[PDB]
Length: 281
Length: 275
Ligand SMILES: CCc1oncc1-c1cc(F)cc(C(=O)NC[C@@H](N)C(=O)O)c1
Ligand SMILES: N[C@@H](CCC(=O)O)C(=O)O
Image (cartoon, rainbow over the protein chains, first blue to last red):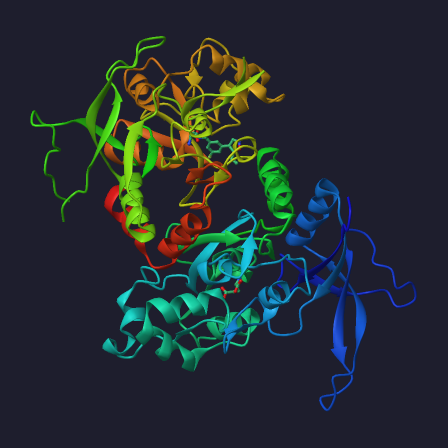
């Protein structure tokens, strides 16, 4: 109960975190949403900016709501502005990871992948969504997985496969560490975001998109005509999960872990999965 | 020097007799890595536990060796004396199985297909998952069940026998669940001492459905064509390394597991022992 009003950072990534504009007449978030603020700059010649009141919802926001109630904390939720999920740049963490490392946030809640390098600088909860690295293609495209030789040695094929990721996250880090030739080749096809990547696929400009498995599976399930698919038997390289990142030695981790495991045991996680993640395909 | 506890559970842990000279049969897929593991020769209920050297290998044993080389520790392995995974029972409250052995200091680390759950996490430290799986149902190639919501499970009788393994975290979950009541208590009447006994009992038409780990059941059906899984994965969850809360190895165990997922080692183990 003591010092239980917590700074919490998140990051938009549907359906895990969805950001809406607040009703301006009321400045109240309604329904299934929670208040979340975003620092927006006045201009680019200045550090001056203002917090905009927004509204947040989604799978991870419902997790936060349950945690808040179960673990008995209140919070001030904000959207990260210094980068995205988390990357080490010149030995300095940005994104949600950076916000936790440098103690601006007590925890980070979102589509944040647990990996070894982040685990060195933050504590992670137990995984609450299963993920890893999947590959999305148009139905019928024959590729075995990340490990396919069309990815590993692309210039052995004529024409070579055109494939990319969204840079600066856990997926790109993994490819950079494991498959150097693939990685340097892929940078040509880097995508600004998931939406751009899906458009590139649907119009024939990219042959595959390599990305977080949970997000790809979601997008595959919502795809018009069920053209975009993930390869293999729901297949995932480097199986991991999303985790709540907490500061090293955090006193909140114990209770957050138990709560998450209780949600799994109680069927509450399955309910959330059915609410947010089920698709037509 | 760490005391490791594990349990017989193919394809994670194979258990075979030593040769007459007390070493393990040389086998090949690349050499199969094997360790000496002590275990009881009497499996029975309420019996004296006479320990004997045996040979242990498989996915969990390869994982152990990787951990020990990575983190520079020595070990001795033994099979859990009571043959069980571990549940908490009223005596006021006591853990059996591998959970009991770790909490008492008989083991320093559990390396086994041990499900991470709330009830165990209250008392021990689990690593990040070394395997993601869930529950499924094993039946005779022949039987037709939709899955866990079939009437014959939901509203059961002595007509259609099904069960899980005793003192597993499946078993106590069914006995405990309110909507499970009629199946909860029904499985109590038929639950088995081990997974191996349950699987053979399905082949010999003594057990019609066996509710258990998908990682074990899918493997069993891949090998024995008279067996099949049915229904979707449910209760998706992980296996974790188990340690006491004050273990000094806990951070490095998790980092090593994360490293192994990311560098393809866990996938290699899946291709060696599971695929
Ligand atoms: C958080 C998941 C959970 O919460 N309550 C029950 C379960 C569950 C889920 C599952 F896939 C397997 C087992 C289990 O008991 N499998 C036998 C064996 N691996 C064991 O550890 O006892 C238990
Ligand atoms: N979930 C990822 C972002 C997407 C990806 O790179 O796969 C992360 O935490 O970095």
